[PDB]
Image (cartoon, rainbow, N blue to C red; front, side, top):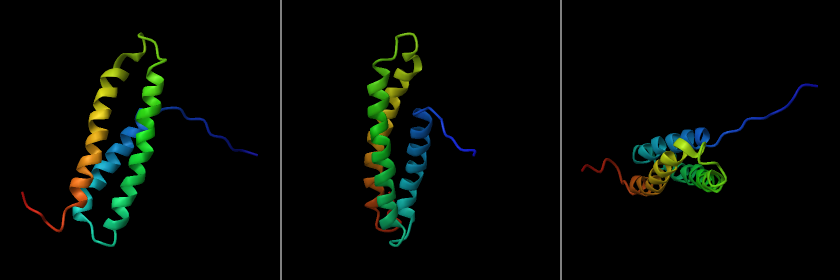
Length: 102
C-alpha cells in the first residue's frame, strides 16, 4: 500500500484559478466558436469554484486572530476586487464577436 493526500491552502489555489481564468477570459475573445462556447463555460466553473473560496476564506479569516489575519485582510480586499471583476471581464470577453477593436 502507498496512498494519501493532505494539502492545505486556499489563496494559492484561488490565485491560480483567478489567473488561469483571467487568462482564459482574455482568450475567450481570441477563441473559436467551438472552443469558446465551452471556454465561456469552463470559466463559469472555475469561477464558481473560486466563488466559494472567497466565501470560505472570508468565513475563515473571521475566526483568524488579529495576529494572523495580517496580509489575509489586505488580500481579501484585493481578491474580491479581482473576483467580482473576473465576473465582468469574463462577460466583457464573451461579448466579443471577432477582433472588436477599441
